[PDB]
Image (tube, coloured by chain):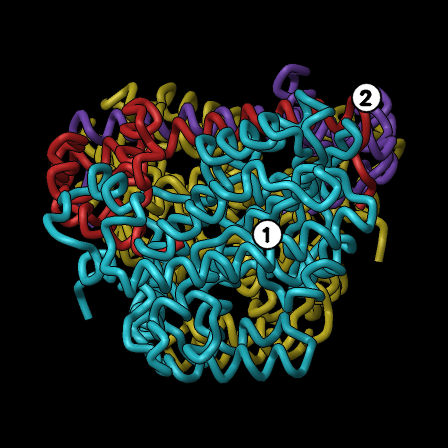
Chain colours: A cyan, B red, C purple, D yellow
């Protein structure tokens, strides 16, 4: 499936390229009216969920905050948010997880188009979901609660690169929000198996290999830059980095809290700030075979997790990681 | 393990930054040697841009973070990619997913 | 893979030397931070020598290769060894085998 | 078993320590006479084998050469010597492998003491075997063949450190020998399993973990120094480095031949010139379990090798690598 929904639903002579196109469609008026109405309806839904989050967080005494959950695809970000940000966990409970700024939250809705069934692929809807997340984020920038206080918001994106991290820091500083950043890491292979466990009937994304590997490289290479921002400015907010131990458990690795910097696991810190690259290394070509499945299973003690890992992997046995994720990603 | 705190934490972080900055520079140096040896197409941002969008929705306006991001990806992450046209398809894929 | 030859081989080797020299220096820097944090006994060659032979049968007459070899081994290779007396037993073991 | 054979068979007030002791016993006269006679007999045997090697090598047109086989314990050094140094292979065939300079060649004989059975451990005989190898080497330095040419000799030792490599280069230069150096690498875990496969009834050494890990670190960290010696001086001789691919096959990785430097496998070259250390990493504590045995077996396709690997490992299942090699090493 090829044509993007931006192309399908855009009106008229679409600028080609990237920027040009981006600006043109950033105007809600350049869409067919039914599509414009669907946009409005999704943004109203997202907005209502984000306000529910913000009123929960303020009622629990949280000053205006940008909670930023950094880290690569399928690293266990949601589980860390839930367990290690108790105020936000309480809020997300009220919205069943909705309300965060993240293009992927729009994809299931755009891919169904109120038709009752998914008829576009994730890639086909991505540009449009990105335009909606940007509009959603723009309307939250100065959004207030019933007390007149700036609303707290949650940015759930990879946040790998310096330009992105700088942009969100600037947004926070311009709107008087603290930044509460939890940065979550897992080894690249853990993200790959995490992606193959995600089911097409779920709403979690299933990207192909290059997305996950290039995401890994970018998140690890730029990590210490993000930590340096907190080390340099105690007033910015707090930073915690969680990494994955050999048995799959998340552990605290480094933190800057109330200005105080500490390294809770120096071995992991050494490891997870580097992409562990070589001149020709290729995990993309590694074939999923019995021993790889057993090698991953050997470090997974929880029965439900182990069974789901195993079944996802067996489905692509004999394929390279690159072939397995490419096939997995192509499912609707 | 025991938590590093105060000056030990700061000195660990400072030394680790130096290590990873050496590794960062080295990875690209060695990749460029290899690329020369195998006759990989020389990285040219303008030509790549004619065939894919590298802007991140116009979020990347600079060419110093932009050339630096893509040229490094081209050489370090994708050593078996021989041509910008091949690389273009990779960049397009990256921007089809969050 | 394709053989690197001539100037490409020499430039690969030169860049790789720089990478591994950074890694060599870094490993010891970071180990010394860690050792300070956990209160590992400070490396002292004279005291170690009172309790094991570090000479390699008198083949190591210098103290610049000698201090450099053992202090580095002590900090980098044996981070969980807290004392020179423990380390001594390790050095004795090394010299009981080819 | 404790007391060294140097202590047992040395006469009188033995200097304590290292040097002092080394010099004292370097004198054949400070041994009990029976022990002195055993020394003489072993050196005569070694000498006769080394001369057989040298007359073979000269008859096959080899100029006076110091063949140096560098590399850690149980890396597959003997197999490379045999297959990749055809002139030396032809010579070693005539002596059944005897004649090389290496303390371990004396150990079985010193540990039996002409008694008919091994009664001292390898560690108990090591100092004395080292004194014999030094005496053997000293007598070979200016040893000539029947043509009056300096004899070729083989130095089969780890040769990890700059001081050692410099000493052998100096010996070669002082006696007009070329240096033909083959440097053989395998991953540390391959050496560890190689050691557990060596049987006590064999003569190959079975050292404990620290020997093998510290050997690995030293051989990898100093490798490029050895290569630089050949790059700088084309007249010194030739250098070839063999590394281990994922399937266990040895492959050429870098070489300096006739002055020409080439990198035949740049990925492996990057890898095998570094010890891959971290601030607290510990392979010594890794436990030999089913999956580790299967993980090693997955990359071994040859039936005889795979079966021997497996049986050696199962014997120590449940133990850490450090406990497994310590127990293995303690066998006589």
Q: In front: A105, or D195?
A: A105
Q: In front: A68, or A177?
A: A177
Pinpoint the chain carrying mark 2.
Answer: C
Residue D169 image point, x, y percent? 40, 25
Residue D116 image point, x, y percent? 68, 70
**Residue under the image location 15 percent in, 49 percent down:** B86
Q: Nearer the viewer, mark 2 or mark 1?
A: 2
The disc label shown at residue A289, or none: none
Query: Circle 2 is placed at which residue position?
Result: C44
* Mark 2 surroundings: few (<14), some (14-19) or many (≥20) residues within 10 A: few
Q: Is residue D62 left or right of residue C26?
A: left
Q: Is residue A192 above or below residue D71?
A: below
Q: Is residue D296 above or below residue B24?
A: below
Are the numbered discs 2 and 1 placed on the same chain, yes or no?
no
* On-image quarter of the N terminus of chain D: bottom right
**Residue under the image location 49 percent in, 84 percent down:** A311
Q: Is residue A257 above or below residue D108?
A: above
Pinpoint the chain carrying mark 1.
Answer: D
Q: Quadrant of residue B30?
A: top left
Query: Circle 1 is placed at which residue position?
Result: D106
**Residue under the image location 22 percent in, 42 percent down:** A18
Residue A55 image point, x, y percent? 72, 51
* On-image quarter of the C terminus of chain D: bottom right
Q: Quadrant of residue A201?
A: bottom left
Q: In front: D143, or A105?
A: A105
Q: Is residue D126 above or below residue C24?
A: below
Residue contact at pointers 2 and 1, CB within 8 angstroms: no
Give the structural element (helix, strand or loop) at label 1.
helix
Marks 2 and 1 sit apart, C-alpha to C-alpha, by 35 Å
Number of marks in the image?
A: 2
Give the structural element (helix, strand or loop) at label 2.
loop
**Residue under the image location 64 percent in, 41 percent down:** A144
């Amino acid at each position: 499936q090829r044509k993007g929904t931006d192309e399908i639903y855009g009106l008229g002579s679409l600028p080609s390229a990237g920027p040009g196109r981006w600006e043109y469609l950033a105007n809600p008026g350049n869409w067919h009216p039914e599509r414009r109405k669907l946009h409005e309806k999704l943004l109203d839904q997202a907005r209502s969920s984000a306000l529910t989050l913000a009123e929960s967080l303020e009622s629990d005494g949280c000053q205006p905050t940008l909670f930023a959950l950094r880290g690569n695809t399928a690293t266990g970000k949601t589980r860390i948010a839930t367990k290690k940000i108790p105020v936000l966990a309480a809020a997300l409970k009220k919205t069943a997880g909705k309300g965060c700024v993240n293009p992927d939250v729009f994809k299931s809705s755009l891919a169904k188009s109120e038709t009752g069934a998914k008829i576009f692929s994730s890639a086909q809807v991505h540009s449009e979901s990105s335009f909606l997340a940007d509009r959603f984020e723009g309307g939250l920038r100065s959004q207030k609660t019933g007390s007149g206080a700036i609303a707290s918001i949650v940015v759930d994106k990879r946040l790998s690169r310096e330009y992105e991290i700088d942009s969100y820091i600037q947004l926070a500083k311009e709107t008087g929000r603290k930044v509460e950043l939890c940065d979550i890491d897992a080894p690249l292979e853990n993200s790959l198996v995490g992606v193959l466990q995600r089911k097409p009937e779920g709403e979690d994304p299933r990207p192909p290999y290059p997305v996950v590997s290039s995401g890994f490289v970018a998140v690890r290479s730029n990590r210490m830059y993000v930590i340096d921002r907190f080390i340099a400015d105690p007033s910015l907010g707090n930073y915690r980095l969680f990494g994955t131990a050999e048995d799959g458990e998340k552990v605290m690795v480094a933190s800057v809290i109330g200005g105080e910097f500490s390294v809770e696991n120096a071995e992991l810190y050494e490891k997870i700030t580097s992409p562990q690259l070589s001149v020709t290394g290729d995990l993309a070509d590694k074939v999923i075979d019995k021993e790889l499945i057993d090698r991953l299973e050997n470090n997974i003690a929880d029965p439900e997790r182990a069974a789901k890992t195993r079944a996802a992997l067996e489905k692509y046995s004999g394929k390279s990681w690159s072939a397995a994720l490419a096939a997995h990603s192509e499912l609707i | 393990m025991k938590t590093l705190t105060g000056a030990d934490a700061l000195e660990f972080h400072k030394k680790l930054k130096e290590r990873n900055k050496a590794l960062h520079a080295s990875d690209l140096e060695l990749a460029l040697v290899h690329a020369d040896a195998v006759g990989k197409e020389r990285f040219d941002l303008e030509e790549l841009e004619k065939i894919c969008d590298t802007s991140d929705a116009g979020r990347l306006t600079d060419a110093k973070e932009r050339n630096d991001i893509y040229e490094r990806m081209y050489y370090v992450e994708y050593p078996n990619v021989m041509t910008l046209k091949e690389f273009a398809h990779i960049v397009e894929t990256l921007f089809s997913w969050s």
